[PDB]
Amino acid sequence: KLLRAVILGPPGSGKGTVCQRIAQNFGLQHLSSGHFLRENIKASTEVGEMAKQYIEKSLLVPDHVITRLMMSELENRRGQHWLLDGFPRTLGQAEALDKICEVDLVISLNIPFETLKDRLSRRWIHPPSGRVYNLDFNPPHVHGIDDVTGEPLVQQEDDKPEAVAARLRQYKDVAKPVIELYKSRGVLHQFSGTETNKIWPYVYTLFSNKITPIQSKEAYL
Image (cartoon, rainbow, N blue to C red; front, side, top):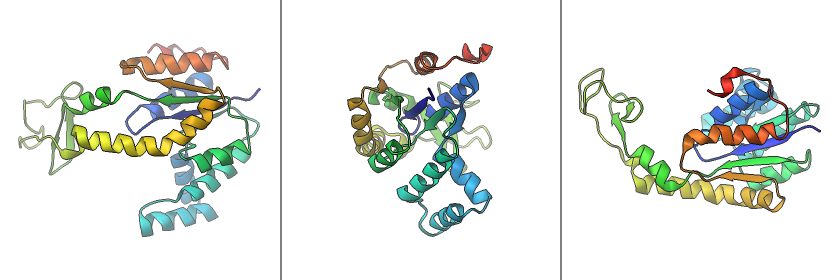
């Protein structure tokens, strides 16, 4: 009856964007830990003020605080369709979620490493300012130099294949137990394609199979 949907993927996969587009196209509310955290901190709720302290003191909000905050928000929404963006991250979080609902749909965006590494291979940066140029997207106005200063661009260590592969492995170590849990329940769709422009229709058809769209012309595209 009510859709319980989750979208997962590593940083830079496009899941925040796809979630928002799904939210507009299907009239779902975009639910994420980041969004509820900001809301709670802004409103100075009990969990909000804890979270604030975690960020200021340790630069990191513990998973159990995110869990607490999500479960309490989702409990105030049990009469609506849920689209969870990037939650559950960990297996304990998944176990908590399963106590409050039956998850019907999990999408994981598992873009091949070769594809992620190639996008990052044409990133150039102006170190002093942090200005970023992707040559296939937002190239500099003059080859090899910063738009503002005319100073040389460089390729940084964070975008090199070894740094990228290490971050990908860290993400998968955390994500794998959740993927396996939902894979076993028959609810899981993994995008592993090379054409990232196909992510949007791939996700869209999976929601169209569950719920009727609000017939926007902003689907294509």
